[PDB]
Image 1: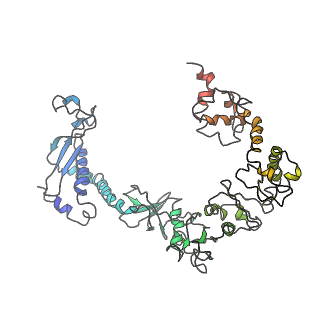
Image 2 (image 1 turned 135 degrees about the horizontal axis):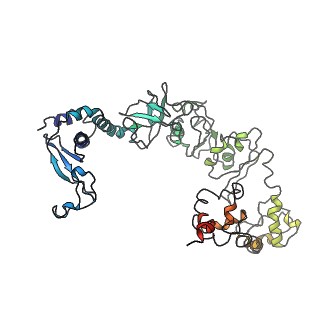
Image 3 (image 1 turned 30 degrees about the vertical axis):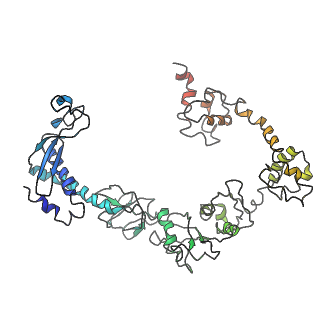
Length: 495
């Protein structure tokens, strides 16, 4: 008997940290592989080694395949008539059984084989605590230096590595600093498994909403959306949970008690969050702070918003580098458009006539009925089946002609498409040779009228600036789409 496998399994400072059978399962197999490598025969070795009573032996695998793989102890259909028809491709049964191999030469090559085996065994326990929480508050102290990254000789029986975009770029996890963030994907790094500290992503920057505020973690403050730069600045909508109170000091701390502590472990930067309230107009105005709001408006007929603010002292409201308004839409849910301070009131300069022309032509009206309330009511008569026409009594004339625009005025909008629908079929458009080819969608070929293409071979003449007006001409939309169309002269007409 071995009389030492039991002691190895019950050392038990290192054996009991991992599974008790790990040493007899993985380390034994690695030792068998090392002994086989030290042996002349290049045969797969499986270690039937147990720490119960010392019954440890080795076996030579058969490697039953359709070839001569592992030829030292290979198996195949050459023994089909002798092994009760056990011919297959992939079977790894034990053809033979070794007795013992002291292998003093393998004891010398231990530093190359068993050292790596012990490293893998340690990594097995390292991965059990590196990122086993699948994303939680994981800290790390930096004690090592690594190229192209930031190393940390932290605990959890493992190391830690932070990429350039993982930790704070201004102050990486280097000697003289520490990190604290969240991570879930931890693979086997150099010298065994390692943890990961990334205190720059949303999972660490936005996690301060319930770690810095004193009345948010108990679900008393509205903290549901927060977009911020990594370790540089943060501008989130600090609101109350339908309390209609001043929340500017809730998530930012009383007298600035949390501005310098939200990301203290992530780099220690200064943030400027925006405020909100229960009023939708006030919340929309204050969600993009600092924004010089000049008017109040809201749009719901389309998937868009309206950022009605100035741009003189509110350069962040329009967006110069994504400082304040970039996280504003996340607090609203709809994308908004902004302009200059004097360009905010010019959104409907010529629109009040452009949209009203199609309503006056359809209803056969004049300027008196086309411009009386066009600038007052946005789309007063434009597909009036949904919009109401019972509030224009004070306007010049009755709203009955505008009320009758639910279907009478919708016929003109379809009859005017006579110069647009026919332009996508044969009016200087692509031919049928590329209208049903692969690479692009069948209906996507109708948008080829903006490049001047008249046939399959005509679309290949577009250079870097001919058809590049739109972003449709992508890599996947041109590398495999025009290949079956423009190659008619090269290899298309030849069967």
